Image (cartoon, coloured by chain):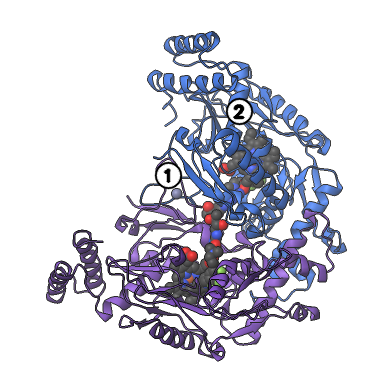
Chain colours: A blue, B purple
């Protein structure tokens, strides 16, 4: 591999030079002969061995002491030595609070699929490594939700539960996101609520949940501590800020009865710091409008409202070339942004977000030597080429610390 | 290893085996993906294997692999490669190689049509006057009074690199662009430089907003020569809108024939540096990129002005609203004039069907998601949800240098 890789912006002619890729740590899925850039996802007891762990820890500790301008210092060498002994005698080690915060912020900084990374240094890290029970997980998660929501002035935050040990004692949030709406399959094949969540809803019901069977039912939390069977908790509904969707011009848009929650909070990913694996690490930011207006509402296998919206707009739906779908899509996203702003809930439109990401990427090239980015995810799902990231060449590679996918827990859990 | 691709909307899973047959590199590595990079980075010795591989798959495609005709064709080609440092393709081979270059073009959403390609053999051309005649015939055939027909015209192959045939125009039909004294740009800003090369070469510019550029044609490595396409061959569509009466007053028009003329066609190790090819438009090519790119005609501000939209904040989505209207106007206008055009919903739907066909009959379909997904309304087209594997099969279309950067005058 060469030391210097160039990327061009085809709209502005700006060229940037990447050296950070020399620190990439593992596989994209691509090869010399095949590109897997559009592929979404390219044993329990299989935990890191002592010989695997030493280099991953040293690499992270080295990186940490470089960041605080103490590389090679006495504190750096003593931390290296203490980590070595801890791995040598316990087969693992514990991060200092400073290292945990640094590692979590850098996993976000390194997330090539995230357009919101200009905020990466401003992340509230909640250390929940003392947690031992699912009730305690629930407490921790409620405090996160209340802190992050902040009455509509949203604040990015992560909560980190105890790391994996032998793989039989994992902490997991079984929910894929902290706040999601239930989905219910009817005997006639139709779905009520969010069709994407039918499987997880059936698990919850089997576990004891009494479903209201409405269109927008907040799912309960399903929380697994120390490898035990997961337990159900209802999030207090006063902690779940929601927005009813209305339109600045179409009086009838409120009659659709749409709403959405304020807080996007991912809870199914794994945080990897210095070889350590944090299998429960819920993190949250705030929404870009297209996540709701295009994907949640207009994906065919989600709420799928395009038809009903186009009918109330009195569009010609007989041909595709009238672009009735595109017309209705824009009006739906106008209503989502207008609703969040009217209720003073943080939200960013896709123009502002992508423009901020270009500024962030240019600063990272200048100050850090690069910025890994997944164009397929960064470009928004509508109006792609009228945002600046469409025209921006990007390089994608995997730096650590990192957020990683992990198996769904109901597939791997051994029931007690 | 076999590779699976999933559609996340339909849950359809396809199995790719065809990638095991590629050799040309993608630019990616195990550590770095270059999927969004637009331009990632012969002799008798290297020529015979490529030639052999191509003849091999040709006779394989006609169910006569290892036949007598096939063996003696390989002898014929080897005999020719050492005694002349090259070889010539049979007509049947040229046609098959051109069709499969289109079939293998990862970035083209239009490939369901790949086997209906009219192939014009111009390998006997020797002068730029001949190139002009061949190109006029192509334009007339492909335009067909608005019932557009896919076509390619193939000029003589590269020999020593000093006698290249080149069409200096990036496309056969483009509008000129002019740098203005105050600093603005009239016409198409992407062609300001190419327009200057034409003006410098003697072209008398009308200095309008939609001036059809002349052909700049280079034969056998000589200086390029200017030619005017007879205007009755250049089909244009005035853009108007089904609802907005004022849209016609924007003065917008476009041409009906998209024809790429700056690419290189590689077949069996031979390099055809002049090979203009043409299809019909997807509406977004004009209404999104040509009209609404900030570096192109850049008309969003004007349209949203006539639409009386609030343009003070981004979150009004005034740009997205005006964008959809412009693209409605394009589709309505071509359709009203009976000029072939495909909307991005129909085009992407056909491409999924084409993917299904290719996995069934061929074991795969190389596809560049970055280029296949349309530049507007991405996730409400089915390709957004389709995983695609990208890999480089030959015969292929490739990029080549701009002629004004290599030419010794
Ligand atoms: C602060 C405001 C934020 C904004 C506006 C934002 C924006 C986005 C968007 C629009 C996506 C695409 C989501 C999808 O298509 O499903 C995304 C993905 C992602 N974000 Fe951010 N994000 C923010 C905060 C955060 C934070 C705080 C973290 C971690 C600490 C984070 C890590 C990620 C990751 C790992 C992904 C990829 C998720 C996946 O692969 O499914 N983001 N972000
Ligand atoms: C017949 C109807 C066709 C349609 C609707 C169609 C559609 C498209 C579109 C929308 C693009 C993207 C262009 C851009 O963004 O600049 C494209 C690219 C391309 N097309 Fe097709 N196309 C058609 C015919 C053809 C033909 C006849 C050929 C060759 C014989 C061909 C070869 C290619 C190639 C090589 C590219 C990539 C160009 C590049 O890399 O810049 N296409 N096509
Ligand atoms: C920190 C953060 C900020 C932000 N702005 N957004 C997200 C993403 C949240 C999210 C993502 C999805 C996608 C599911 C997986 N995809 C691949 C199908 C949802 F469904 C969902 F409800 C949901 F809240 C996370
Ligand atoms: C066979 C074919 C069918 C189709 N439907 N479309 C095309 C593309 C043609 C084209 C492409 C561009 C893009 C220029 C290069 N890009 C990277 C900036 C033009 F500008 C242009 F005028 C133009 F006709 C080709
Ligand atoms: C097949 C394709 O990779 C898939 O549909 C991707 C495309 N880009 C995306 N981009 C974002 N931000 N989120 C997604 O879920 C997807 N889905
Ligand atoms: C940087 C990026 O590769 C570039 O802007 C691409 C993105 N996708 C595209 N897709 C098509 N069809 N045409 C293009 O010109 C581009 N441009
Ligand atoms: Zn790749």
10 Å crowding of disc 2: few (<14), some (14-19), many (20+): many
Q: Are marks 2 and 1 on the same chain?
A: yes
The quarter of the displayed image where residue B112 is located: bottom left
| Left or right, A264 with reference to B149 | right
Disc 1 CB within 8 Å of nearest ligand 7 atom = yes
Which residue: 70% across, 29% down?
Answer: A141
Q: Considering only vertical position in the picture, is B202 above or below B289?
A: below
Which residue: 44% across, 15% down?
Answer: A91
Cβ atoms at labels 2 and 1 below 8 Å apart? no
10 Å crowding of disc 1: few (<14), some (14-19), many (20+): some
Q: Position of residue B261 (x, y in %)?
A: 46, 73
Disc 2 CB within 8 Å of nearest ligand 1 atom = yes
Q: Nearer the viewer, residue B80 or B73?
A: B80
Q: Considering only vertical position in the picture, is A219 above or below A337?
A: above
| Left or right, B364 with reference to B196 | left
- Residue of label 2: A104
- Between disc 2 and disc 1, whose residue precedes? 1
Q: Nearer the viewer, residue A166 or B409?
A: B409
Q: CA distance from mark 2 to mark 1?
A: 24 Å
Numbered-mark total: 2
Q: Position of residue B90 (x, y in %)?
A: 24, 79
Q: Can residue B110 be seen in this snapshot?
A: no
Task: Please tell me the numbered disc located at residue A29.
Answer: 1
Q: Where's the C terminus of chain B, which quadrant? A: bottom left
The quarter of the displayed image where residue B276 is located: bottom left
Using the image, name the chain to which the residue with label 1 belongs.
A
Helix, strand or loop for disc 2: helix
Q: Nearer the viewer, residue B288 or A174?
A: B288
């Amino acid at each position: 591999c060469p030391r210097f890789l160039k990327v061009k912006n085809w709209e502005t002619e700006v060229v940037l030079t990447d050296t950070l890729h020399l620190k990439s740590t593992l596989e994209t899925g691509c090869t010399e002969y095949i590109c897997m850039g559009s592929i979404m996802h390219p044993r329990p007891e299989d935990v890191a061995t002592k010989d695997q762990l030493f280099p991953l820890a040293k690499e992270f500790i080295d990186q940490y002491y470089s960041s605080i301008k103490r590389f090679g210092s006495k504190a750096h060498m003593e931390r290296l030595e203490e980590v070595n002994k801890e791995i040598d005698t316990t087969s693992t080690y514990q991060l200092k609070d400073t290292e945990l915060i640094y590692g979590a912020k850098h996993a976000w900084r390194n997330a090539s699929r995230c357009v919101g990374r200009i905020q990466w240094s401003k992340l509230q890290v909640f250390d929940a490594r003392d947690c031992t029970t699912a009730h305690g997980m629930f407490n921790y998660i409620c405090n996160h939700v209340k802190y992050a929501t902040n009455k509509g002035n949203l604040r990015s935050a992560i909560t980190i539960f105890p790391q994996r040990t032998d793989g039989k004692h994992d902490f997991r949030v079984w929910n894929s996101q902290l706040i999601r709406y239930a989905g219910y399959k009817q005997p006639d094949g139709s779905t009520l609520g969010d069709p994407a969540n039918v499987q997880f809803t059936e698990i919850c019901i089997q576990q004891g949940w009494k479903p209201p069977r409405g269109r927008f039912d907040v799912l309960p939390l399903l929380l697994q501590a120390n490898g035990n069977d997961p337990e159900l908790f209802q999030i207090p509904p006063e902690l779940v800020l929601e927005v009813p969707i209305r339109h600045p011009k179409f009086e009838w848009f409120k009659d659709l009865g749409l709403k959405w929650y304020g807080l996007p909070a991912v809870s199914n990913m794994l945080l990897e710091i210095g070889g350590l694996e944090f299998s429960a690490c819920p993190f949250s930011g705030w929404y870009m409008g297209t996540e709701i207006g295009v994907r949640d509402y207009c994906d065919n296998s989600r709420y799928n409202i395009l038809e009903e919206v186009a009918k109330k707009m009195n569009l010609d739906m007989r041909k595709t070339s009238s672009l009735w779908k595109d017309q209705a899509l824009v009006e739906i996203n106008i209503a989502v942004l207008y609703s969040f702003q009217s209720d003073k809930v943080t939200i960013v439109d896709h123009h502002s977000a992508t423009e901020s990401f270009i500024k962030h990427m240019e600063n990272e090239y200048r100050c850090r030597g690069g910025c890994p980015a997944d164009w397929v995810w960064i470009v928004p799902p509508m109006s792609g080429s009228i945002t600046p990231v469409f025209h921006q060449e990007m390089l994608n590679y995997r730096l650590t610390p990192s957020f990683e996918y992990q198996p769904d827990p109901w597939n791997t859990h051994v029931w007690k």
